Image (cartoon, rainbow over the protein chains, first blue to last red):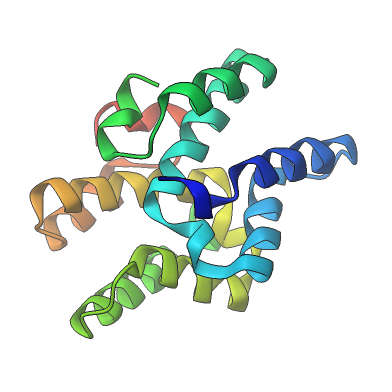
Length: 84
Length: 84
């Protein structure tokens, strides 16, 4: 499960950070979320989910649909990096 | 470039954490390094390199070769995850 990843939170932080036109929002939110909730949010399978969603966005430039597709399909296993 | 990523530090922390037989060293090391140096170590390209290196390691379980192979051929572009 990706419960402890606090992924919805990262999504809101990411959208809000970019509304401020801050650089490297992906880094800032990971740091912010780590400082509050720690290692649970940096598990490699959280990283896989975030990379599927964030790659989709830098390339697809939707966010709305990139979250739908990731949250419904990507579970965090190492294999997901090449169909997501 | 990937200098701000402090990747060799992460590589040493992971090796140290694993030699102690602790679980979730990728998370713990990402976390401690975050608490110490911050968002520059969590930029999306650092995550690309870390994923190529760590994926090569869970699948093949070599480490030194996965490190050398990733260090020489991965620069952090979003397109690197196709051939790590």
